[PDB]
Length: 237
Length: 214
Length: 11
Image 1 (cartoon, chains in turn cyan, red, yellow):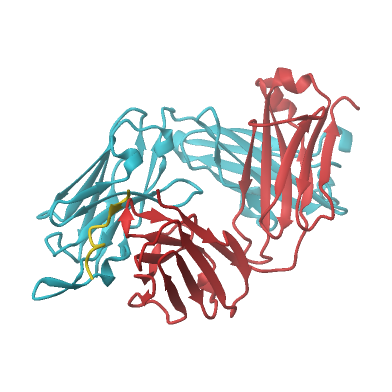
Image 2 (image 1 turned 30 degrees about the horizontal axis):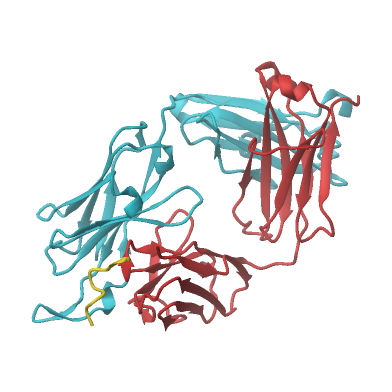
């Protein structure tokens, strides 16, 4: 019944201004005491409260960001806008808008606080990245199986996928024929501002002599595709 | 300034289990406390509002309790969809505050990680940098520590870790730690070691190579 | 002194 959806730019440069819009249905911002709030979630971290605006144009901001935050509404458009100035990479996060109920009313006057004590419907979230990086395809390097990567009759190998922007990258093994024992790790953002990840696979040490192993890497934003064959170092042969 | 402290920050359990998570507030927030469940890739979903009120459409297995500074969320009988992260939020004071979250995962027998170390490839070294990779494979529980030493010098600030989601089949995690150095620096040293600490190991396990021994 | 919520004073 109630729905909210965030929109905005996926990518913004440092020092610029970020404008996010929340469009909603199922409630009206002229409903007594209703609120629309914003919350964000940095990659791998917890929820962080940003701001709230109410039907009477009352507004509140996170104290540590109140110099950069501005919240506004258009009641006839069923939209709320959040503006964040002077962004930095610290502001990379998924941004959620959310609905807060007004109080229980009788004859339009409040009789109970209860219902207000939660954000009851959330939007799906929008990912925003703050970065000064330019599009760049990855370099692919091998993680060669070895004596140093063995577990009795089990060996590990992989591909190191380095220095790309933006996300995301996709990795398969042997054009998709190898899926078992594959672990493709979430990307990390490096100090350079570029991402990197690794995919590894465990296989039988006995196969290393005969079976071929190739990681297929596709980075669509740079139209870069790479097939990287990974094999034992010469000394292990 | 208001702090909300959730405990535990992590717990494991099994389908059918009953679990309890607590939130403590540094100041009384009356009954103004909500509980949410969030699954990966999804927004938080409201379970309980006003400390103890069950949100419409929420399964009856969820319940909340408490008032003032101390609050509890209870799931009477864990279901598969309840493996997730849980947050509390207080709405008595501005700014509204969320707790740090409590991750609930599938319990299984303790499993020590298999540790592998990977030197940088000659190909990468050609381009001026060296990445050394330590892989911890198929362990449980999730908590694990990795230390890098280069010729016995502790490395700090030049590595990054990545962990997988819990495996749907065997319920384990894997983790990679990546040490980054300049080619020049990599070639000035010999012994590269990562030391792994985990509950399943009687004592910390060290995997290393000596690029000066050939 | 922290500021009170919009509804902190409502029964």
